Length: 387
Image 1: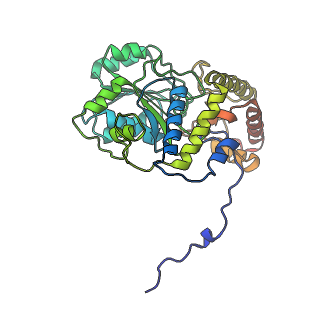
Image 2 (image 1 turned 180 degrees about the vertical axis):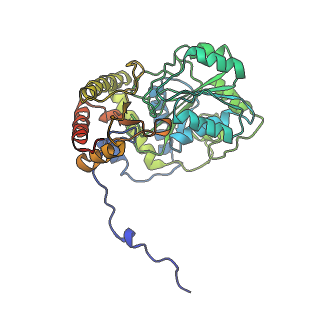
Image 3 (image 1 turned 45 degrees about the vertical axis):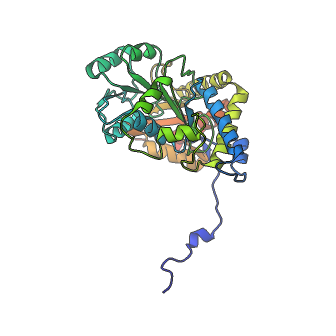
């Protein structure tokens, strides 16, 4: 006759969060403007004002992406969710999907495509590698894929993919080009239209400096027809593009209620898109390039090595560093956070326990932080147990 569970003791305490300087593959630290937005009040999830805020965000995504695609919007989910929204709406069960599996992401793409019943063909490759225009034709010819997936910035390996020539190829094969720019957006050159990408998506917590939880996505006219001419209903409802497109003002139809968008998070995505708009896409590109260079020399000076041997393949936003000869990589990471309040990750997926990952994202991609982390790494090398 009573209540099984009583108020949780811990909840009766006040929320207290440590001070952390995040310099890993993400998320990144939030700027005062973004933090301020996140502290504002609610408004109608379907009020004229949300729509404006929503239309402003669309414009921002078209800016950072460099596209005019009417079908551009925010996915109410993390980067992963944007990937599924793309795969589940584009691939019909049995569509033969070509995947560039050179990191954990392509593998994530395979796993998803497999789950949605697509004939998936993985183009494997050890971590650190990228894909030639050549290696892809073989795949395209051997499997006549309807969709091809490519990771622009492998935050998993530190590799940066060249995207040039793929329009060419993909059209020469009637294949849609899907690119992941969660880790590259804002840190290296990218142009949807110019580069012929049919589906582009990115996260909000990387170089954009917004809190995790939302992601950006854009579909070309080509991608559209597919999605809109499908005879099968995509397995997902939450991510159905016809519903999503309409609510975000991409149709000719009035805005229908689908799901309630994350209002507070949109405030912050705005601001973060207005911030990068103030810099200028190209200045942002210099920052990360220049910062990434500084970091590289500084790191090589400490005696460390760069996993990615080719400087032109090095992802500015995320740098992979081979794990030093006699150290337990776990000690180095813990030593950095325990003594410097700084985050740096180890590897992820194929790169697990093979490297350390240091990120330079948005307002954080600075010489200042390159120094701060450079010195935290020294101490760790000096004081961590060595075989």
